[PDB]
Amino acid sequence: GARQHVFLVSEYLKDASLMFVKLVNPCIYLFNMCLQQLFEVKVFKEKHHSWFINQSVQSGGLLHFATPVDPLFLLLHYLIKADKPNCILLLKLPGLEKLLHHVTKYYKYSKEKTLKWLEKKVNQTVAALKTNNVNEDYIRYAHGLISDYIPKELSD
Amino acid sequence: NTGRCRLSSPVPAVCRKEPCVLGVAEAGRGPVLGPMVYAICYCPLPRLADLEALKVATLLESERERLFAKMEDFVGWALDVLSPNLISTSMLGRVKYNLNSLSHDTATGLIQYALDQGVNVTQVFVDTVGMPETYQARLQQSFPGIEVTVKAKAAALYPVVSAASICAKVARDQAVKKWQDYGSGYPNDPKTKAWLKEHVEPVFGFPQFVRFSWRTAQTILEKEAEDVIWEDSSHRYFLERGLESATSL
Amino acid sequence: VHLRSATLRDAVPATLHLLPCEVAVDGPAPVGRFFTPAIRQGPEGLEVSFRGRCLRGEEVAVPPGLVGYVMVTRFIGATANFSRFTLWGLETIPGPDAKVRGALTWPSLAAAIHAQ
């Protein structure tokens, strides 16, 4: 038969009170139009696994996750190339200008502001590593987590 | 019962006091279909004259049912029927536990059972297929206090083994009659080969009654049924979690 | 790809099993004919068998505050919805430090990573 996808979407996507686009990786994304928010896609691919959906088989054992994303990482590639396809709809969302004033009518990229903003996320992920309890030594561990979402991490 | 199944007759008063003799013989070792049974027979040493009349050397299905009825005051029995799913799971498990070692651990179990019930066993007879030298030494080391004897001609040599063989053969027949057109059940039979091929599921394969562990059962699955691959045929965080960034959708 | 919330709100419940083996070709399978009547409730979860191999199962629920969906294909409609899935392991139930168990801890961690 046809191809099936096992997803784990956020609870608020059920009520009406969404589109999937292939945007360039900063290092597939889901975006809302009615609610205005950007989400990333993550697939769980383990060697030797297959699903048994009701009365049908699905090889691979792929588990997709609809997890939120801060647009500051996605929109960063647009001003990273200067140093000093579906990308158009990605930026044009309410409350973007106030969000822009952390990294970058006129808009200019800054390194000093980006360095302070990235240093706050490391201290923000260190608490998640303390809440979810991931196996201080957390400094390099929390730094390595943001490195999978930005290419400037090599310089940081 | 779960995997295997043990059916037993109550221990007769004579067995617990007078010195007894045990016999071990199997039925259903070679078929791809159905379960495997193991039966033991025990009688006091002076009552060997009575069993001398109900001993073979072959016997027909009607005659074996008749012989089983006579054995059923001094003669005691115990069965051990291993399901075809249990046989499939024993051999196909992550650690290979061959039919030879599966059959022989079922033999030592029933002998222990008789010793656990209180039967005054002094000597044990065993029926094998090929070399008994390695089989005798293993059962002699397991039961050091009793004289263990293993022979391939045991069923034709002693009446205790023939009675234990009739009990294993009738139980094997009763079990397949309870399930009931395949033929005999053995891989060599062309009617059996024809039945298996007509009962193959692309995802699942054969039912519980089919011993998958057999080379005959494993070959057919590779042709008709779908290919199934098992466990044996920073970047560090996601590699340890088995997660990766999506690009497929 | 794009799809409404009406299909996500009117999706019938589903039964899911995560096998530790891969079944190469997708399509219909008679689960309720072979796998379902084979399932045995034990002290160490559930026990069934596939291709003559003993499997030990354990019921694994969707992370707190989330819901599981099964999508089929631009528009990709949700054919069904679930709250839990049966996790299976070869000979013994999959341990606490399994790759499947690790990925479920992610949205709880991800809720504080992308925080404002």
Image: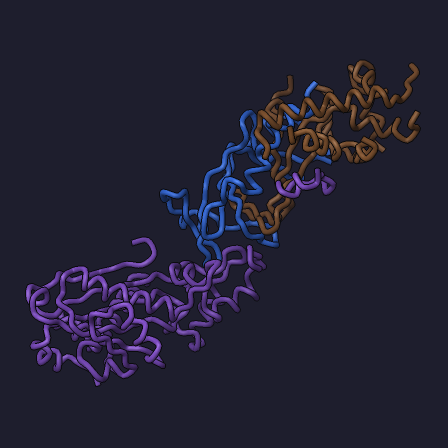
Residue A109 in the image: x percent, y percent?
89, 22
The colour one sees for chain B in the rendered image is purple
Colour blue belongs to chain: C
Check the image and report above or below for A147 versus B220.
Answer: above
**In the displayed structure image, the side of residue A105 where residue B3 appears, left or right:** left
Check the image and report above or below for A155 versus A12.
Answer: below
Check the image and report above or below for A103 versus C36.
Answer: above
Question: Can I make out residue B73 in this image?
Answer: no
**In the displayed structure image, the side of residue B57 where residue B13 appears, left or right:** left
Question: Can I make out residue B184 in this image?
Answer: yes
**In the displayed structure image, the side of residue B68 where residue B36 appears, left or right:** right
Check the image and report above or below for A23 versus B4.
Answer: above
Look at 58% across and 32% down and name the residue there. Answer: C105
Look at 18% across and 74% down and name the residue there. Answer: B123
Comparing A52 with B238, the one in front is B238
Residue B169 in the image: x percent, y percent?
26, 72
Quarter assignment of residue C3: top right
Query: According to the image, what is the colour scheme of the structure?
Result: by chain
Position of the C terminus of chain C by quadrant: top right
The colour one sees for chain A in the rendered image is brown
Look at 45% across and 65% down and name the residue there. Answer: B213
Quarter assignment of residue B54: bottom left
Residue C95 in the image: x percent, y percent?
49, 43
Considering every residue shown, the one lying at the far bottom of the view is B57
Residue B67 in the image: x percent, y percent?
16, 75
Quarter assignment of residue A125: top right
Position of the N terminus of chain C by quadrant: top right
